[PDB]
Length: 376
Length: 48
Length: 114
Image (cartoon, rainbow over all chains, first blue to last red; front, side, top):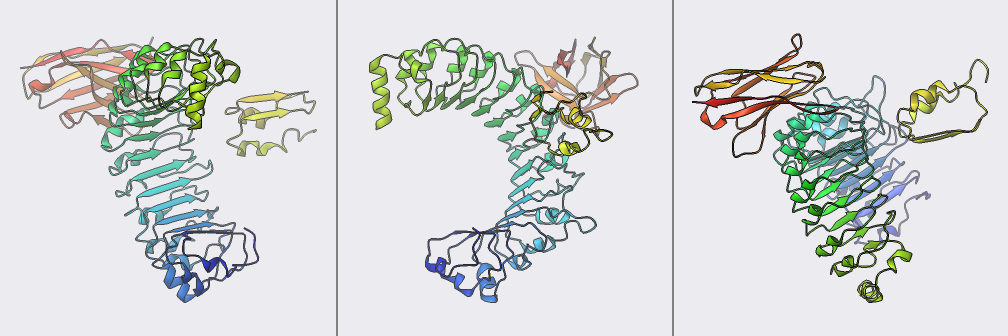
């Protein structure tokens, strides 16, 4: 970070695979970079490096990840377009320009081997070269830093894509083109100001959709139609305006990750225990009063986040869960700790989060056993 | 300010991820920029 | 005041067509997503079709996709569901569903296939 140039001793290793050069002016890529052949990741932050023919030939076959964070258009080296075996790319910097839009990325076409492309470049609209390179992509990440992103039938043409992330694209409403991507398996739309997500009724067109991410939005209510997505295992809808949970949502018995923290929840439906594969529960910062009995049906509940909740008493069924690996209780108005929590074989002191002045309320035998299990 | 009050802070509309806001300026009127940007604010504090 | 009423149910032969009309009063049908579900005896209620609020995008149950047709007329604030190529496997009572602040299930119309 912030050196005069490339030291010549850094070529002393063969165990290197990630190189990160940031704010290091006028670094010329020597042929001596051949001293490390297994290197596959390279970070060039705020530095357009000058390259040599042996170095370019070496990089044309033995590089996989290139990170380009640029304060200027000229800070992007041109020669990076010549590489053929690249598979991970990252372009950070506001390349959006008037009447020369997405022209700095014209050499992206030759990256046939590419599978991963991440974009944090304040792109107001979807670039055409992105559509060109989406014929064979496996992961596309777009981050506009809250800028409104417009597609208008330009994202459905990436049939081979397997992961889609449109973070802070300010869509405010799901575009239909995403439903055309039948190969798409996991979708992330974090912080896009979503208020009505009934478009999930089209999600049945995705037969391998097992994870959905629509968190950090203004979603008021969860449509019951999400019960049609039985495949889902991880569902993320926390940081929203949800006060009630539809019962039909609990038709997806495959659900394993259910995080709904920072919401207006007050009751946990009796159907929450219908999901045997439920492994992670997170309702932190809510108004939950008590744990429903069915919530203990999931014996493999390996995570439990109950913090900042108004629970009055801890149910005694918690000891019936033996796969409990971690649970946080800090921030709750509990009179005393039930001893059943102490009978979990997988539980540890570090796994448990609770106030010491109440943690001492447990009998000394249970506390000593917990400390011993924490030690080794 | 006079005839340009609550105009120098009109850039507050650009901070989309702004949540908290505390103002201690002996004001008499709610800024229009703050009025528009408060749709996503979680806490607004004023100490006139 | 949000009221969903179903009309057009009854008995119909296999391979025929039937019109199910869902009428709404309290809310406009132009800006609201509408849903049609069905329930058969010995089986929990099953979703059939859904219609959007923008773009006239319509989805249907894969078992009956292409067999039924859902449309809406905003002038009468109604949803028309035309069922074609009927078979005994879809003998069920069909309900109109919406969520406007709260859930709203319609009266429903039982269609039997002979």
